[PDB]
Image 1 (tube, helix red, strand yellow):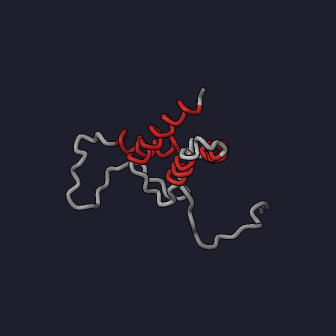
Image 2 (image 1 turned 135 degrees about the horizontal axis):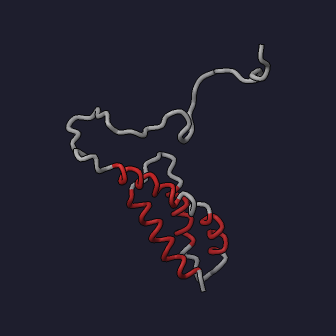
Image 3 (image 1 turned 90 degrees about the vertical axis):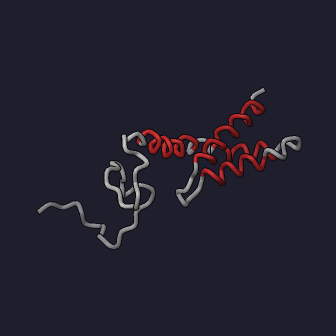
Length: 118
């Protein structure tokens, strides 16, 4: 008789950002008319789309620090809305992040970097 698992209990299930479910292989359609990938060339686009969410998912933090050093400048008071926005965007809890926001955050944060580095 082992002795170690005596403190927890299986009561209800509730995942949190990739915990229980893990959609990997896409070879089982369910929606009507699904021929947007006959040759099977849509994995790198489905992977980068999610990989891009994770790409800026890192820059989403540095923004918080910027929001302070930015509001700190009366001349760059306008940029304050850029960091707070980018951060408020990339933090989308609906898991609905279109390449438009990702690409914009990357392009925006990039243009804001050139002005931050003197």
